[PDB]
Length: 49
Length: 98
Length: 49
Length: 49
Image (cartoon, rainbow over all chains, first blue to last red):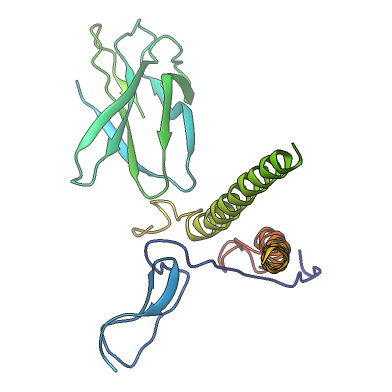
């Protein structure tokens, strides 16, 4: 299938689950805490600055 | 009385219906009690039987595939491991070549 | 009777609203779960899944 | 007050309308993109993707 019409990819996420999951590479300056999903919304985890 | 089996990986989850192995019989004498069974590997690594079938009737002297239908479907999921065991607990005594 | 009919129509619209919201959430979560899981490498190709 | 409440309800319905349409478009496009992309043959199985 050498050449093929490249369909423009589109992705969406409602952030309405238990954990962030493996679909998100997480990197933070805190060291241990990353972006955490709570109440159906992504947010900051921990009290660190 | 000698049983041999190998681990099988599951790529995509589905329902299994039959199992196959490449084997034959050495001599043309009558044989029985040849069983092909399936074992699921749990988290601890223990093997649990989830199906077995007698294949001695359809065996042939020539090296040919043996395909046998399970008594019922056994749902499988990707990431787990399964073992297809050949038992060969025959009474006459003819050996089985796998 | 007019106000009763308006009450009934508003209740029907609320039912449709909640059903549509639940269906949207379930559909998006189904998309994400299917994307997360799926094909895994067999035992002979690799030790790990 | 009745007309003000009707105004508020109509604005809420319009917000729900646009959100639902956007969610439908996003979900359909995401599914189409996922179907278009996906598993590709490894290097050893074949040269091309």
